[PDB]
Image 1 (tube, rainbow, N blue to C red):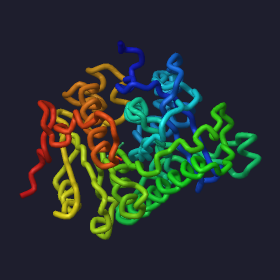
Image 2 (cartoon, rainbow, N blue to C red; image 1 turned 45 degrees about the horizontal axis):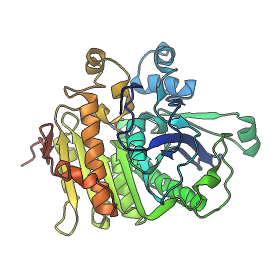
Image 3 (tube, rainbow, N blue to C red; image 1 turned 90 degrees about the horizontal axis):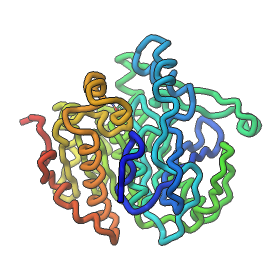
Image 4 (cartoon, helix red, strand yellow; image 1 turned 45 degrees about the vertical axis):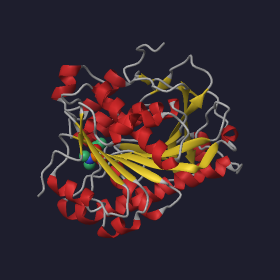
Length: 377
Ligand SMILES: *[P@](=O)(OCC)N(C)C
């Protein structure tokens, strides 16, 4: 039945996927997230991928390229869509498991739609947070309630750090990110239990649809690279999250105190080319006989294989810009997504058929490695 439509792949699951944005409150300390969810309507595939010019300006700043690159990126990618139905109604059905997703350094909430849409197509609600810790290439917020209804945006761009700042600011940021993940969860749970919430963005989607929609027993946190460190910090702080999946986690931000505080299952899915010994050693600090830990490495992949820019360009250009690895981008994301589904079934107790991919958790595939290729004897 399935066939190619958008550059970013459609979900492999049985459900069509809707998408909307939620900001509450309006401030630099409020929650900002992009929601993906099972929808009934299948037509539209009309969610704009990068919805504001300032994100392209932010990406240029993050890349350290000349100011005009922002304009060029906007020209190239400003009309790009992702295969989700903008503001489509939530599919009625059984309570849905929930994932809170954390983006990497230089990213923002909309850049992991291949992951969000795949999860939603298999029956998850996914809340992709936008962080206000100055790790996003760009984000926005407002000065007051009137500026929200008026729409005078204040933009906040990635903070570049001096070496002496790395050694404390990254930790401050990961703690803020964990707070933001827990706060996003609380916001979604408030909406689930019927607390009125006023979206600071004016959008068609009525949040009251989400009343009684969440399976409060089946909540996980997933994140890429800074987001992988965020997974670990969040699990250590918030037991409402029952398991975590870290995608090419970047471990540098984390303090030593976190490891002993994570009873929950944790899955590391790594790229072949990003990882390095100092990082792997910190992953190993998470291992203990009393804790469930799994690790796989995707053969021929780079850290950008987890993010949507891996689909944005052709093979040759993508490889040159290190947006693509040697492996095909759909092969890689399918492995990550299927292994994730199996892990989530196992540790959230889902009554689905994702256990068909149990072997992927063990790295048993021609394009996977159990554990790591990195040596640190
Ligand atoms: P990570 O947060 O991945 C970039 C999206 N990192 C390499 C710091």
